[PDB]
Length: 255
Ligand SMILES: NC(=O)Nc1sc(-c2ccc(Cl)cc2)cc1C(=O)N[C@H]1CCCNC1
Image (tube, rainbow, N blue to C red; front, side, top):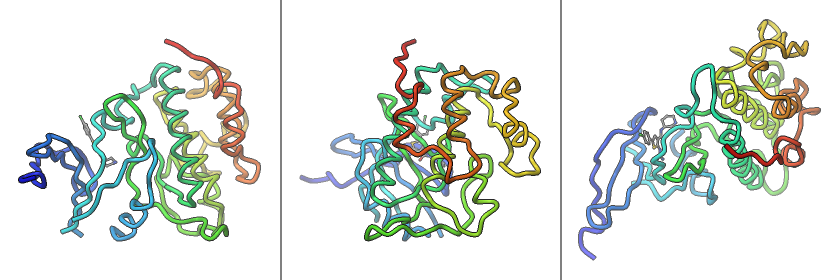
């Protein structure tokens, strides 16, 4: 078929250093194009291993060009109303989808390392897709776990052990960031600048002062889950299999 390989760049999508929408001249199929002038080699290699409904699909690469599954719903960040969040049933559905994507990644030995609402996209049916694997790395290979030591991610979303320890397990760090995402969705506010002993908001949380925001805005059920996720000691922190057994996680919700 002629012209089937021709794509038109019709509009600029987002940051990076640029995300553009490409439409096939013949089929009208759409794809997102990640443009980086120009690290990228690894992002491509990891992307090639991914195949899950809650992870942005990688089509190929042709400076460097990254061709990805187009998510017309944009960033989850934009569905969060400042100081409000979003309806609990919507937050729960997004959280279920986030967990499914994270379980998948962890199952293949990959850690994202930068989970936050700006890196969680939504498709036309509002299905959540984990995006931006520029910081991702392998934490398990040949059934052997490798400890992480590199400090990376985004401050308000990073787990405390990253700041305090020379080495740390990958999985609990991603679990922690998911908890910060859940907090944002339910409160429309991040709980602290960073989980440091010098941060008053973090000290307040460790002291269980849940009568304060953002906690006060969150229902007891999801709050009880957050109490299990945002645990300082990563070895005591709830794991995904246990999150799947949580009361709120399993609560039927409807708007
Ligand atoms: N694969 C894909 O479709 N990506 C999209 S669609 C979109 C989009 C934007 C606006 C609308 Cl209205 C619809 C879709 C923004 C981004 C995107 O990747 N943005 C990156 C920027 C840097 C932080 N991570 C996210």
